[PDB]
Length: 11
Image (cartoon, rainbow, N blue to C red; front, side, top):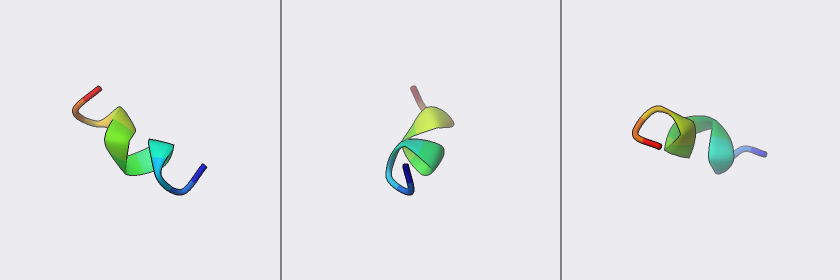
């Protein structure tokens, strides 16, 4: 979930 957190901003 630490990778999706930041990847959420663009995606």
